[PDB]
Image 1: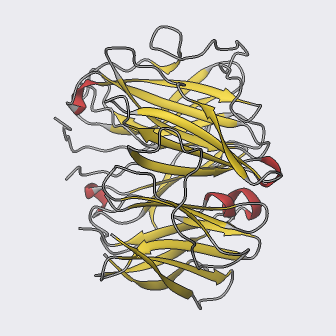
Image 2: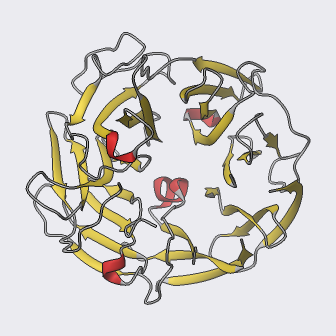
Image 3: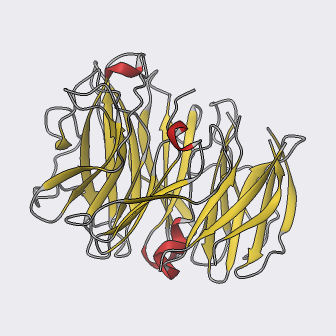
Length: 375
């Protein structure tokens, strides 16, 4: 039933309709775009005109156009669109809004209701990283700025964020704060959501934010102090009811051992729960565990990770119900993928409840799509 489907060797996975798209850098450093029909193993692979840092984000809009952004130097925005619906061929680089596009890192697309797109990036044009958010309107075929300043670290702070657009079109946002250049100064887990494509933001209790969101006015999903081995830049999800779930890891005050965690809000309060039972300490001050990924089905969680304790396999922790059920931990591979961190086809889960993972041994190594069993 589970399958490990070959793509190609390389030095980011999205379904639209019955086709799955992928992006990676080949051995010669060229950005490749590929697609297959679902339930087949034949990839059409298109080496683009662009050569490689090395972050690629793709998304397909409601018309079937592929939008692509890549971060090499962390300077000018690199943004292209396919020439036609369904095509892997890219046009020339183009602007989005033409404003604040000179110092771009960590591009991320998300799909919105009715075929529109969201774009989030880390802008460096102030001298420090700042979340900038744009929307692509399918009806007028242009990009517009949604927020210039959403999370404000004032003089004192950087933020590291993750987002998810749920099955109702709500934008979920969570982040950690970081005080200095040192990773040990990560602290806390904060939350916001928007029901109106990023115009207005709320806390989970229904209180409306007055923007920007600072450390003073933020909703704290969890208070986690500095020196807790709290990692930055993970992922989050939501169920069909719009309840948010955040996956990360940190170490409790009394323990030497960091543990994977799930943090979620049930409509009334925040909960957190330990996911596995690790025994090996590590400190962030080659990290032996990966940043986690999650998919959810009404409280049932599939939590994807990688841990030196388990031989650096692709691993899964699964619970039938995050509120009450035990976690069953298994390996999806029986081979090490070393420094790999999970990513998955977010749209395929939302539309079809199939979990597909981008898998590659990470230090040319074969890229695979792992088609996991979840029911």
